Amino acid sequence: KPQFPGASAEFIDKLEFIQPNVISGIPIYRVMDRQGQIINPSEDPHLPKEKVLKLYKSMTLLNTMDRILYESQRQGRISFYMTNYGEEGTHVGSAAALDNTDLVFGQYREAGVLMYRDYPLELFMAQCYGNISDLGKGRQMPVHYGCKERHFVTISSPLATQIPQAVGAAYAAKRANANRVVICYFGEGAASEGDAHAGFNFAATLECPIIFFCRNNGYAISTPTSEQYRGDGIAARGPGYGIMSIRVDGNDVFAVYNATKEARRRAVAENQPFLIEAMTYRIGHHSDDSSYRYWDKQDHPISRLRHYLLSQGWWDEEQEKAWRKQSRRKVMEAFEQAERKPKPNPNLLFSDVYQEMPAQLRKQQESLARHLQTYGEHYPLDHFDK
Amino acid sequence: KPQFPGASAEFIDKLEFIQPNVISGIPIYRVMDRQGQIINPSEDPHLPKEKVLKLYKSMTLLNTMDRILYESQRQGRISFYMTNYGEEGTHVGSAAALDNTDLVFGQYREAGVLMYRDYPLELFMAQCYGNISDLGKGRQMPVHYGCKERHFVTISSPLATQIPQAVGAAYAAKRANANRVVICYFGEGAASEGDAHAGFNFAATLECPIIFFCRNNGYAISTPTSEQYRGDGIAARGPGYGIMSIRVDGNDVFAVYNATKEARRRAVAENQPFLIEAMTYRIGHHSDDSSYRYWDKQDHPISRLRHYLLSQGWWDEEQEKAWRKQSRRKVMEAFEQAERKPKPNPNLLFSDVYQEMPAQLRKQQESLARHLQTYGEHYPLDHFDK
Amino acid sequence: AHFTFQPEYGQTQKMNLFQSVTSALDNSLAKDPTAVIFGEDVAFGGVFRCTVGLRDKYGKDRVFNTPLCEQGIVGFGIGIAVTGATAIAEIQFADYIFPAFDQIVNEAAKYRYRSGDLFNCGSLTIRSPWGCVGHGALYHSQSPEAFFAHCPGIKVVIPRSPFQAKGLLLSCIEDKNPCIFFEPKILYRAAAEEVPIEPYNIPLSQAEVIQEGSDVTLVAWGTQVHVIREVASMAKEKLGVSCEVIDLRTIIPWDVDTICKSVIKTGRLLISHEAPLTGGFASEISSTVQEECFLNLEAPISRVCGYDTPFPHIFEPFYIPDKWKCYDALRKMINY
Amino acid sequence: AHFTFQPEYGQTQKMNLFQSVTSALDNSLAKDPTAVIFGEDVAFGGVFRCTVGLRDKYGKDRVFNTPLCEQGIVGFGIGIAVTGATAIAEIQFADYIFPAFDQIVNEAAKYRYRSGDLFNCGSLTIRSPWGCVGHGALYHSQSPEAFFAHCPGIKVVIPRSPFQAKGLLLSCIEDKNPCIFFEPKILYRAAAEEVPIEPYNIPLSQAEVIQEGSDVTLVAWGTQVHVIREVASMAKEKLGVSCEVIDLRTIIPWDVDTICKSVIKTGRLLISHEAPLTGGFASEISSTVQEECFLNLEAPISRVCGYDTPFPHIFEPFYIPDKWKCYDALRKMINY
Ligand SMILES: Cc1ncc(C[n+]2csc(CCOP(=O)(O)OP(=O)(O)O)c2C)c(N)n1
Ligand SMILES: Cc1ncc(C[n+]2csc(CCOP(=O)(O)OP(=O)(O)O)c2C)c(N)n1
Ligand SMILES: [K+]
Ligand SMILES: [K+]
Ligand SMILES: [K+]
Ligand SMILES: [K+]
Ligand SMILES: [Mn+2]
Ligand SMILES: [Mn+2]
């Protein structure tokens, strides 16, 4: 019997290399087909009508906002934008399975989580426009959302940095014994970063209640997954870290919901991490003219959820028309209001660098004030607060 | 049928999380037992007598050098030292399976690879003493060996940095089409670094002829593996990256040799990486009073190889005695000579920072020369060259 | 924008900055069979089009994408260079170079020294978009040169135009030391200029006096050179002040002699850079100049730099050391 | 060695530097139930014994080992701090802090700013052994403070003795900004001194004039403070020169007023640090002092620093800015 402390195993007397199983990888969990039909009754979550309608409306409201802000960027009204096309179901489905106070870390494609948590259209817009209503004070590029009230940690551009951070927040939650989980979203490209290896390993060895949620949409900007990794996607990496893992159909809100609900339940009870890899397809551009490269007319999360609603008698064409009209109205009202607000006071460029403001930093702020007194006509002072 | 570009798999209609298999991990490949007996004839490599005696003598000569340099440190004659106790077989066994020109990257416990490649005792000593014969010019701490002639890349202290580097060297070898492999050694602790995730993934996606050789001895200084990872050791991580992997009994030079020989053969032919995890036990201290914590009287690589020699009639007590005497003599001759050599010229502190020497750096070197002209009595000038 | 671009080796062709980078890379792969180019999204031409057409022309084994991992990109590059092959790595935005900081500072920079020259990674070059772009905010705007300036063993080079970029980049690729080449991204598409079609080199560690002056010395690099060139014009017209304008070009090892020689003549110095004041590279230039020209300095050296804060989105117009800020400090310094 | 150590709050006990760190950590976990300490090998007491007995006293869930991964240690620490819990991370040697450079510079330092203060990691402190040790060579000797000084949003603090270390470390742990605390390892076991058993604080961003003087100002931090204290003695005895000796203590935000006020009085300044000259923090102090005290400076400010090379093994005695090197530069400066 092998006595090595590093592993638990039997001896083998024949030389055999372990081959990866990639052609036949971890199967994709599915609950409803492309026609919105429940495939296996025992897996139907039987979510109440009001909640399913909220899943639907959240993801179509997000889609309406995406269309409008995407165009706004094209016109140079906002400096940058990233859509959520094809990611709507992974976000609303997983957000619906969380408790309102579960802390969320993510990056660029999680707006739907905030939408499900009722983040105001006015605040999505304030951040993209960097106006006076932005609690982020206009400091970050557009779509770098954050909400303390809705436990959505501020997004940052450096990929994967939020992964080991989410693990630390989960360790602290374990200690506070508040029966809270942390969920951390990231794409399959970001999973190649060293920080992903750091977070996955720490979560397992430090026994943290965290759900790692990987959105695998086949591309990281122009890079196909064939150039991103050679194993069986990201799901197959979880067991190597001792992490309970699963792969789901990301265009199926119910598959996503069921996997997330069960992961949250076990993660909080057992203080162990879970990895969910949601297979999807980035329908829209990365940010970038996508056309280095079907999922809109044959396999779209919104379309599948809509068919499900119809089969239950929960939606119809007139309701569809009225909602498209109402959501467009709601989004355009927030948009116009956002465009008209002034930007924050230029002095806000100096606060929050440290909690307090160092004297030498105050001197730089005074320096600017003096500069503007004399050269102000050469600056856009009328567009900024005070 | 699933149509996602990120993975190849079937749909599954039942929610099932994938559980890691750690209690029954990847089995440990063994060729001979603790009594040096070949367990399975079909696995005997039937290495010629001269080569097996070289494996034996290399690892006992290394052990003799270890004892002496370890004591030297204790006395403050050299500033630092790291032994190879219990790692002797993983190193000679794998080095014997490589071609002389295969490039080696490693860290602290690979001295046996250099020994097998006939690195002179005089050069091991010159580096530890940082004397004039050191081609490294006395710049690095002891045991940071390097040899261009024997294709052993200079060791550096930052753990795991050599991993993605070894991958790049392997990519370049692929392109040069020289039918060479690269082997990269590292411990199970170093495998937790982000650079390990970087190298493993790049080697698979860029199809590189490299062998990753992980020495898992159950500890990284005071940290047991239970606090280092929770999956089935390092071997189980290889398949998740699409890497052919295997685990071997590191105290069995023949298991190590067979696994390395076969990995080298396939890596060079197929331009694909292989991962070998050698299970061992760090018998000596980390560098540190090991006594945060059997393998010397019941399972030692040297002892097992010795029993094998006896069963073939290739060694005996008198040969053992004469060799212990001769190797001790050889090591003490190098040691005394090393201690007596002066250190290099202080000017060598300035060269090789860049290939050429920047004018501003020359000015600093002139500055020192002037300083020493005046204050030289306060410096150990007589101990250094010129 | 906030600057205006304006301005022997054979046939030339009009090229903007990104095209001049492609030209330098093309010349390199053509004359050096071992050279390879790699990084995130370089295969299809790059997010800033610097590698367009190179994969089709040279092969998928020479111009290829790596997984999304900066520490791996640099460690991988070091390894290629260790075998003597030319490795030209791309880091997508300079702001994302930090994950590779350990591989750059602890490994690349120390590779030759620590091995007694038995091994090296001299044939490694890391290129990366750099500097503000009007709306880049915290992570699409950084100027990390001062972090690298404190690391012996690497060279850090920054061009100010298409002509300068191709010549300095070819010198970096051919230099026998690991080099970091920062490409001012706001210039990628901004105004083209004539650039030789064939390879030529511009020396490293050599500043360029682009306009002689006798009253004060102005030093900058990258896009900021255009800002001080304009400031020189404003000073001459509004104050009758003659400005000597110098592009540093190489951050380390820097051209100490050119700067001191200029200050010995003018007796005044103003250094400017987008990067934050504290710990910025202007502090090193100022210290050194004070030490070499104490006798000639007629006033305190001034540094007009970005503020000591992260780079903001909506406040960028108020953050950058623009021509008015440089002008004002110059005015006060001239009146000292 | 190359230096000599020498030198209200209740009962005190003799403590060397590592014991004073343990005392500060013990006081912190006792009064702050959320505080946890983690990193490589901290559970058994640490490779430099700074955490001995803390796990037994406070629990395995509060003093624990992490996997061997610096970028993870810091990202993990940031995350704990994001929930408001006190996170005290250890990086085994300052030389190994670079893998975490991106998490420190792009994340920790910018966390509060970029979120409009909706989130922060103010309760994070990173402590790490620092400085030369006689034979540490390239990776057991580094002084990385200047790399971090160019990053707005973090504080970098370095003590010179056991008393200073416990007071500055408690202030770092309690400060509402992410702090990096560098512990001069050569002092861990070198000479003890009286240290209060109970918690006390020493302010951040405040330099300490440890000896008044009127002829020249000498500035340093860490072990180098002891070197300049001795240099002061040599100057007084061999030259009749009165030296004002100042320990900077906090690298950023630094105490600009104390240094300028001192130089305005003495009119001369010599700054010294083990870290390499180029891009070293002395260049920032010198630049700033030149800008604020141009009228009072009677000679060029001198910087006596480590050379612009990696830190060598066998040549250390010739590399460090020892008392003789500082003395000589002081002599020349006094004779200016
Ligand atoms: C450290 C870092 N490197 C590079 C980038 C540039 N970048 C932004 S998004 C992106 C692609 C990420 O792909 P993925 O993680 O799969 O997410 P997706 O965009 O497909 O949702 C890249 C390379 C970055 N933001 N941060
Ligand atoms: C980046 C880095 N972090 C920390 C250290 C300090 N250190 C030196 S050896 C070591 C343990 C490594 O353990 P392992 O990789 O398992 O190798 P072993 O010593 O057991 O052969 C540590 C933490 C280092 N050298 N480099
Ligand atoms: K992030
Ligand atoms: K290494
Ligand atoms: K180069
Ligand atoms: K703090
Ligand atoms: Mn993707
Ligand atoms: Mn180990």
Image (tube, coloured by chain):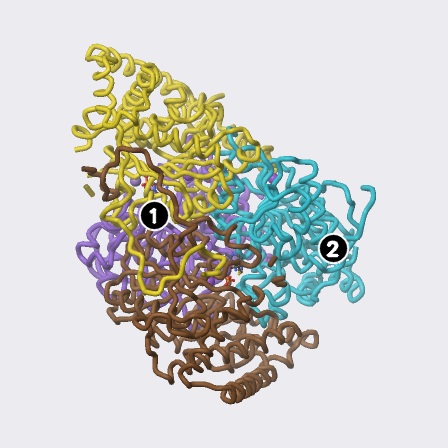
Chain colours: A yellow, B brown, C purple, D cyan
Residues tagged by mark 2 and mark 1 found on one chain of the structure: no
Is residue C258 visible from the viewing direction of this image?
no
Q: Name the residue beneath numbered marker 1.
A: C68
Horizontal side of A26 relative to D54 (left or right) equals left
Horizontal side of B162 relative to A71 (left or right) equals right
Q: Is D123 located above or below residue D189 in the figure? A: above
Which residue corresponds to the image point at 70% horizontal and 74% vertical from the top-left? B378
- Judged from the image, the secondary structure of the residue bearing numbered disc 2 is loop
Across and down, in percent, residue A59 comes to 30, 23
Q: Name the residue beneath numbered marker 2.
A: D16
Across and down, in percent, residue D144 comes to 56, 54
Which residue corresponds to the image point at 62% horizontal and 54% vertical from the top-left? D46
In the rendered image, the quadrant that contains the C terminus of chain D is bottom right
Across and down, in percent, residue C40 comes to 31, 49
Identify the image quadrant of residue D35: top right
- Which residue is more in the foreground, C260 or A287? A287
Q: Are marks 2 and 1 in contact (CB under 8 Å)?
A: no
Report the amino acid beneath label 1: Leu
